[PDB]
Length: 130
Length: 144
Length: 139
Length: 139
Image 1 (cartoon, each protein chain N blue to C red):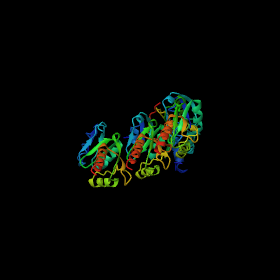
Image 2: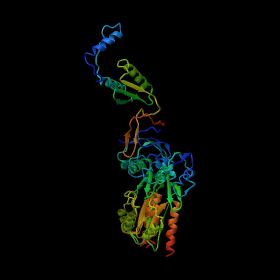
Image 3: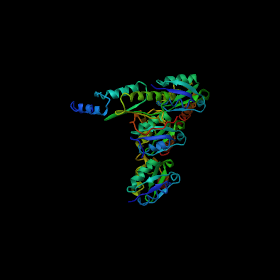
Image 4: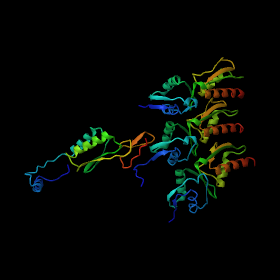
């Protein structure tokens, strides 16, 4: 969904990538779909029950895992990220595991006169008194 | 250099006096917090898009009483509510209530309980409201 | 829904948590604030729960129209008061028309006489005695 | 072109710097002289800057015609007074012609009666009570 090269100028790229790797015989080029690379990254992060946050923008996505995670949520998030970078790489989707001292693991709310309103994700976090 | 995006007041262990002073611009009147009701604390991120509903909901979750007499907002706590019984002689409750309605001190949360055409009734509320109702009711009998 | 998980709370910080489902402010006395209570409670009808808990704990309460007062049982005071020119039917109709008539602590006495007997919470008896000796002197 | 650069002043150091752009001297009380302020200000419209700062800091102010008195909000007093042989409309017509009429703290009461209610700064209430009681003794 982001490349606009024709069939004639896709064999030029395959013939030029063949000259870079002298051990190869013919480089096969296939077009992977673009929403499957973000859906597998989202559903694999929901399956481990990890508090995450998705930020969609043009030309790549990102998933942020903030908060005071415990040892099981760190070992499961690090094992899934290292089992995903092998398959798809880090050109499109990037993970953002970071530890801060707030008991709400990423989310934030403000409270007035009707209940709670879910705030937009920002960089500033409220420090947790417990 | 204050990085937050929206609007609101963030309180980190405030003393319930600087909080209600921060709500004193959205409320267009100054706020007078009492001495015993300023020993409580509050912590969180708040947002005042309309203040008269937040003040009513916070007065019941924290436990407080408050009164607005046209110029300021007096805030007490629940354990300071005082009451009194007053007996008129020549003016009725139905026309003293017209004095409160014409002036602007009528408060529907703390009305006057009593007979409509009589002289004795019962009032209970904040100490700035009771000490006004008693002093004006016993100053209208000597006027008439 | 709603509720309040109390852990060693002390009956002044507990009834203020019920002071939102009840729509009136709650005033707890000093002797009734020494007792403590724990557990997970659920507020969906508070006027049926405060009646049962004021008997299991031992308390008396009263709602005068603007707040709810709570004392313990050993704070009840009594009074025997007399009237000179109005009867019991005038005072009971004054209480029913004003709205301070409490059906659980009524006035015991002869229906056409001057004397009766009041017994209840100290904010109820201090109103009935004052409004009975300040009303007959008006006439 | 003008402006004060406050670095940890004491609200008496600060408001005297505004006493040139305001054309009247400023008198700050000693309980409202404990609060402090910092920042780069700009005195181009001080009658709206004094109004905005008195609500953010928490203050009440009154200008009678010679000076500007500034109190903190916890010094607001109130009083109820009764006039025997003059009504509220001629006393308010006295204040409209004497220039002591303050629209922020008006007089609450019946429009042709003797009893009314007043609240504001301690220099406004102590003037209004003495001026109200010094006309009935004159009549």
